[PDB]
Length: 230
Image 1 (cartoon, helix red, strand yellow):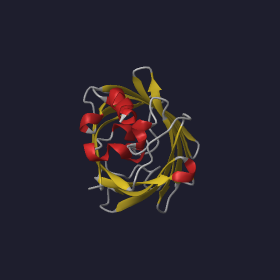
Image 2 (cartoon, rainbow, N blue to C red):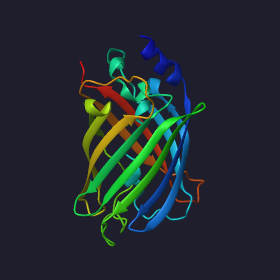
Image 3 (cartoon, rainbow, N blue to C red):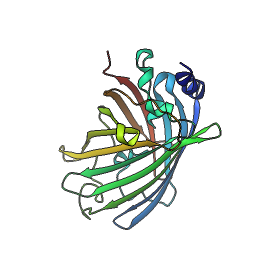
Image 4 (cartoon, helix red, strand yellow):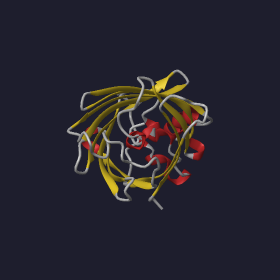
C-alpha cells in the first residue's frame, strides 16, 4: 500500500527528536527543551528534557503526556490504522485539556512534524486555577509513572482523531492525583490520512535522572504499542 510505504520510509530506523515547550501555569513561566530519538519499529522513545529557565514550577511527571504518538509500534495487521505516521511529514496538531481533580487544568497545543530529518514537537502549555499549595504547585507528586492504555477513536467530521484517558499520579502521602486527559489531533497538511478503527495504545514510561546533569531535568524512556484490533 503506497500510503503505508510513505510512513515506513519515514520512520524505518532511529529518528532524532527535538521537543520545545513554552509554559505558563498560574503566571509561573517556564521553558523546556528536549532531545532524543525514536525507533517506531520497537515503539521505543528515549528523551531528556531540561528546564532552561531554572526550576520547573510543576512536577516533571505532570508533563510526561504532553512531551510523540507517531513513534507507536503498530503491528503489521494494524498498519492501515496508524493516523499519526500517515499525517507525516507535514505533521499534525495535538491539543489537550488536562483536568487535575480538585486542582487546576493544563491546556496544550502542539505541532508535531518533520523539520528535515528531525522529528519536532513544538508545545505551548497554559495552566490555570491551580492551588498554591496543592499537589502540583506544591510539588507533592512522586517521581514515577504508571502504565496506561489510551483509546483512540476517529473524529471523522474533523478529519482526525479524539482520545480520552485518565492518568493517576502517585502523591507522596500514598494517595493518587487523577489527571483526566481530553485530546484531539488534526493533520496540518491537506493530503489524505489514515482514520483508524477504535483501538488503543499501550504505554510504559520510566522516569530517571542524568547523574551528571545539574539543571532541573527529566530522562524519559517510553515504549508504545498499538493493540485492540485482533
